[PDB]
Image (spheres, coloured by chain):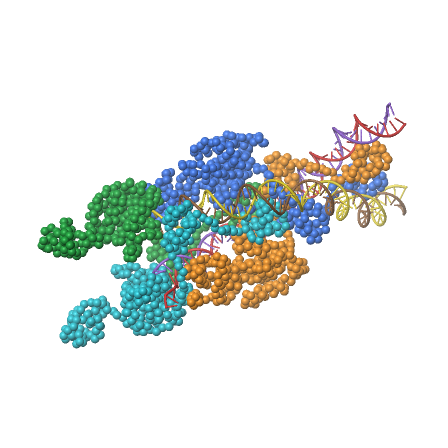
Chain colours: A green, B blue, C cyan, D orange, E red, F purple, G yellow, H brown
DNA sequence: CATGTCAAGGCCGATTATTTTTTCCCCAAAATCGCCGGTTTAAAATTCCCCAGAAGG
DNA sequence: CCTTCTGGGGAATTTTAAACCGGCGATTTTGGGGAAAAAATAATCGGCCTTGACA
DNA sequence: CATGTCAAGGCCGATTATTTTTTCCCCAAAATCGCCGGTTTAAAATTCCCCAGAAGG
DNA sequence: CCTTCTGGGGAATTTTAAACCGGCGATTTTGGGGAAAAAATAATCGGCCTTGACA
């Protein structure tokens, strides 16, 4: 099959009026081919034909069943399996036929969705790994909060993912935004959800009362479907692939301060690809309504019996309580920072006098 | 030879009643020349001399080989070579014998032929300069087609010199001139040929399809632009590209294609009127930008910064996004055209399209 | 610069004896270029020149320090970092310069080694994942043993990686091979090693006495360097990428039997790439010396006080012991399979009479 | 014209003492023709007639354009065209005027020229059949070079028709013939040109370097093999390829290159003796298979099934593994040659090389 | 002594089978080209009258 | 002193050569059908090289 | 209501700067080609003697 | 009856035409140097599209 140059030359020659024989002689082409290409508006082209039958055709349904349902993409395993079924072919066929399927595996169809301003705050955790601070190992964890409409990323590094730490980071994110969105999206975790009841979302009483105090509602997604919170997950693959990779830190406060400056610099004002607008100039389009702060900092610790005069001794210091506690046993809760609380039957004692009779 | 009139007179005198021998004695010519020319059926014209043998006939095949394949026309190199091969002649013979072939070879370079009606259309490009459209700089380009015979010029401003703009401007030129010419010749450029090797050219696929659809043949082989720029663009007021093209076409119709040449004294209009352009097809070629685009598994496929969302039926596949020069986008999936999605000519954020599809589906 | 075709044509024409001017006219090339190419044994070529200076050159040492020591390969992070240092360039330079480094990162140089016959048996574990058998979840684990010289892979699926299970699988592999190699290579695990002592390999007393009983020596590799046992690790990436992917099983014995048949079919006789010889025809070139089998199947369970007559009751059945145990408390060890043992002060009682007085 | 002898006699008679008027009266020729031819310095030869005007001179440029660019030589198409353009003549004029150009164009196809000494070497390939070497089948191929002038044939058996075998066999042919010819012409094949487009050819890089190192030029343009196979290979006993090549060269030296042609009556040996081959360079080209190979980070890089181990200095890089046809392997890393690793011609397992390096390093 | 290894997938090349395209051969019909002879046109040559110079009555 | 002859120039006609036109014979070209060969595309089989994954 | 998303890397194209190659113009020198005239060679034509046929003394 | 003239054939020489050789004049070609333009390679900057990763 001659190429486009020869066809254009032939058309030129005939339009010039030359004899077919002279065209054939000069172009080194037969006269009949010249004739064919005279009256042919279609120039030479690859002209792909229809795929014909193949040795693998009768086995293709089984190959598809193995590939999709079972999930097999090893060329030789399927070759061995179908050799027992009468396959009289080689392995390159199987590799070539399977290449598209293995290239397009574990990929479903997904529905893109955007929510309304101030009505979806995605929140997620991440165990970054193991780091050494002051010679002591710690399992550091990112906590990330992304506002759905504005994509206003906020992140904080913590040492534990306890309920108290979760609530503290959530409040920090809220005051960072300036308001509490009505719906907060989370993942299936013990703190957020006690469990499941026949596919019914369940939330812990503590978290429910916390949210009622702060006027938001959890909206945990489908179990085992963590793709739902794509915003926060990709905000976590941005922090990790832009900030942590190459970060030098010595103190946790230093790292958090580095992260917040990095956020305000590039993470909160870089024009988002999908929205095309900087997050900071859409962070003011979300309804806000803040509230004061509260916490439940407590640790189950030693007890002390209160004398009949209302005085009890702790670490050599004298503490006086109301006469109602005289003769009863109380729980003294001292944290590593020196904060001291007193409890009785699980209720915090709000009135305490510290008489420094050392 | 001898006078023909003498031969005819001798024949008549023999037929007059005079003995041949007496004729020979009187005329001082033998009786047998008289006898030979008496039976002459026709007058003795130029003697038939048969291929007088020369002094280089044996080497004629060698010299022809040299000239026609080796290409050597000097009369000294080959003179020495034939001397080595046993040549007993001189130089004038070789010079005279090669002179026809020498002039034939020279004529290959004296290309001073005239283009005949409808034969070829010469096309030229140009960077007009730098202009600002909607606050963005752009290197606008002039595109000038020129009929070889009528000399008329069709000029237009286009942002890009890409293949699609080339095809659209060729269509416009054919419409303006009322038909198509046999051959269309350009300057060596990527949109036409994918390189050349000094005598042969590798034509493009889409360009060749276009050319054979409009019945012309491309030709990239090895001023009007500068005149247009010096006489129209300089000192011209315009704020729109469409208005500028309108003004250029008006100027062309008034005082460019109707400007008589000093030598010929005829305006281009009459020359075009006496021109032969083959008809133009009933419909026009689809010069829409042809671009294959993979559609992500979420349906979001991006084209020139605009991310369109499709349905799950065609997610994960590659589709041909034909973009018409006007701005309309047509998506074809394995030949089966898909519903024309919203094509409002206002670049909008992808989240807006997410919302649009989310509300439309439900 | 003309191409090879033009240069060859020019050489042809001059060898033919043509004038320089005629060559120039016919080829459409200037006479001086023709002259240059007449006497030039070097034909036209790409002729790559030397790379010149670049805006990024003064910053390249810092980029290399970030890439290798810190380990940063994000284009924009380094762009931002070096923009503050006076970089007046774009980002494509940085991406292009960094592409080779990111393509060749986390790759050291490694020394290939082969050991002598019957002197290295690599052994490793793997937690395959979570599977459901009879409606009950189980954390299945591969145990793989590869003989260094023969590459004679053996594998067994287990439900736990306890010390007893480890020893049982090791013995099964040994009897599969027919002999105990002198050196057995393991990984840093609690069962194999109690701990570390200033970079000194330490082994548990139980495992040490076990190996002495079976006449082999542990040869645990460098800590944190699990690359040392490449043979077993790739034997584990062969089982997973050839057998488990697409395996249907309902009972653990069925799965182990499937695996052993698959081994004997393709895993033990497929010609190894490096050695070029089937493992089965080099499995007979390794020294062997087996020994009988032993185990420590015990479970800490309930106790029973022995009466003064030597009889004690368990689950309604009467058991008689030697008079030495009269009046003492013993430990009855009953497994789920009904195996019953008796212990006293940690020592198993070997003499017991079961009087079925039900 | 009139007789020159008459003019000379008249001049002498006037110089003899006879009045011009009396001469005119006697000869029946005017006195003034006599006067004109009396002062003749040289005899009156062919009259100088100046470019007799024809009936198609205005159209001569058009006809030349048609013939030399359009290529149309028919005397009917152009006859009608010139009739349209106002042609008042006939057909014989056009036929005769084109006959020179027609025969010149025809001569482009009557390629019946003789190859002169040393000019071109015609090379041909062949699949000899199927043979078994060391228990493995192989499609051996014959390679036959042929001098255009001397007609001698150099034939050799090679397993592969790859480029390196081609270069080695060309070197052997040049050594056998004692020099190199100007041009070497092959059949269209991948090892020489990367495709052609009917008039132009894209030569290879290594092949061109080789050709310009041995001072010849390739030429792929558009029997001896079959004779060799029918007269030597049929009914031949051999168990080695080297022995077969030795026997073929012996046969060529005895009764193939010394077999007189019936027509010429001369053996090829004398024709070669009277041949001009340009000298051969002092050294030979390196036709070692050029293959770039990435070296894994463990130093194990594989070539044709053999996995060699290198040192950490060159681990992770790509090296050029030049394989000489003999079997030796030379590794070059960015120009700096590396120590020639063990190259025993016995394919050995990779574990053996692991052991070798492990014991050598320590 | 401590030392990383093995396999799978993809790509390239070669071989075989089917389909499409190109090339070659024979018979019949048509068209064009070349050579020779005759005629026509253009160019060249020759001859016929007046002015000037030289020679002879 | 004068007359005649000769030489040169101009115009017209004739002759010769070249070119042009028509007819005949030979050769070449074009169209259609059949068979064989070559080229292009798709399918099939085996081997080699490099990279990746569990660590 | 429940619905996956965002960024980074690589590639392509365009623009700018530096280096290499190619092309063009002017002056001086050298070589080759073409035309005209003269000479030589080959081919063609013509003329000069013997045999045959026809006509006239 | 016979003699003379005419026609045809063969050979040699001469004439004409074509071709060949040498010299002169004109034109074309080649080599070197300088300047300008174009092409190729390397470097630089911005944008777009697709894929991958934490889930
Ligand atoms: Mg492990
Ligand atoms: Mg998560």
Q: Is residue C21 left or right of residue A340?
A: right
Residue in the foreground of this view, choosing between A198 and C160: C160
Residue in the foreground of this view, choosing between C69 and C280: C69
Image quarter where the C terminus of chain B lies is: top left
Q: Residue furthest bottom?
A: C323
Residue C109 in sight: yes
Please determine whether, in this image, residue C132 is positioned above or below residue B216: below
Residue B41 in sight: no
Quadrant position of residue E10 = bottom left
Q: Residue at x 77, y 37 (%)?
A: D1
State the count of labels: 0
Q: Residue furthest front?
A: A358
Q: Is residue A112 left or right of residue B64?
A: left
Residue in the foreground of this view, choosing between D99 and D360: D360
Quadrant position of residue F10 = top right
Residue B350 drawn at (x, y percent): 34, 43
Residue C156 drawn at (x, y percent): 32, 65
Q: Residue at x 14, y 51 (%)?
A: A355
Residue in the foreground of this view, choosing between B308 and C262: B308
Please determine whether, in this image, residue C297 is positioned above or below residue D160: below
Image quarter where the N terminus of chain B lies is: top right
Residue B299 drawn at (x, y percent): 35, 46
Q: Residue at x 35, y 40 (%)?
A: B348
Residue D173 drawn at (x, y percent): 59, 60
Please determine whether, in this image, residue B116 is positioned above or below residue H55: above
Quadrant position of residue B106 = top right
């Amino acid at each position: 099959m001659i190429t486009r140059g020869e066809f254009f030359m032939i058309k030129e020659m005939y339009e010039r009026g030359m004899s077919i024989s002279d065209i054939a002689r000069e172009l080194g082409i037969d006269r009949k081919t010249v004739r064919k290409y005279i009256h042919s508006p279609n120039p030479p082209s690859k002209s792909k034909r229809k795929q014909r039958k193949s040795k693998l055709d009768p086995f293709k349904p089984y190959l598809q069943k193995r590939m999709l349902e079972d999930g097999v993409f090893n060329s030789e395993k399927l070759f061995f399996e179908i050799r027992q079924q009468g396959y009289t072919g080689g392995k390159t066929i199987l590799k070539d036929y399977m290449k598209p399927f293995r290239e397009t595996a574990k990929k479903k169809y997904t529905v893109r969705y955007e929510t309304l301003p101030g009505e979806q705050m995605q929140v997620d955790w991440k165990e970054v790994g193991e780091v050494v601070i002051e010679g002591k190992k710690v399992k550091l964890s990112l906590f990330v909060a992304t506002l759905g409409y504005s994509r206003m990323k906020y992140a904080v590094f913590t040492t534990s993912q306890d309920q108290e730490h979760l609530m503290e980071c959530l409040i920090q994110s809220f005051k960072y935004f300036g308001g509490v969105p009505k719906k907060v999206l989370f993942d299936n975790m013990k703190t957020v959800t006690d469990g499941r009841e026949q596919g019914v979302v369940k939330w812990n009483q503590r978290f429910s009362e916390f949210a009622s105090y702060y006027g938001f509602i959890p909206k945990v997604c489908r179990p085992y479907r963590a793709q739902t919170k794509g915003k926060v997950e990709r905000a976590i693959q941005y922090i990790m692939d832009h900030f942590y990779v190459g970060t030098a830190f010595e103190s946790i406060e230093e790292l958090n301060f580095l992260l917040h400056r990095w956020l305000d610099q590039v993470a909160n004002r870089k024009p988002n690809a999908t929205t095309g607008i900087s997050p900071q100039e859409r962070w003011a389009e979300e309804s806000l309504k803040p509230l004061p702060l509260k916490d439940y900092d407590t640790s189950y610790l030693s007890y002390r019996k209160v004398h009949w005069d209302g005085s009890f001794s702790y670490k050599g210091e004298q503490w006086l309580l109301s006469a109602e506690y005289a003769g009863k046993e109380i729980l003294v809760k001292e944290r590593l920072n020196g904060d001291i609380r007193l409890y009785f039957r699980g209720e915090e004692i709000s009135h305490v006098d510290q008489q420094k009779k050392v």
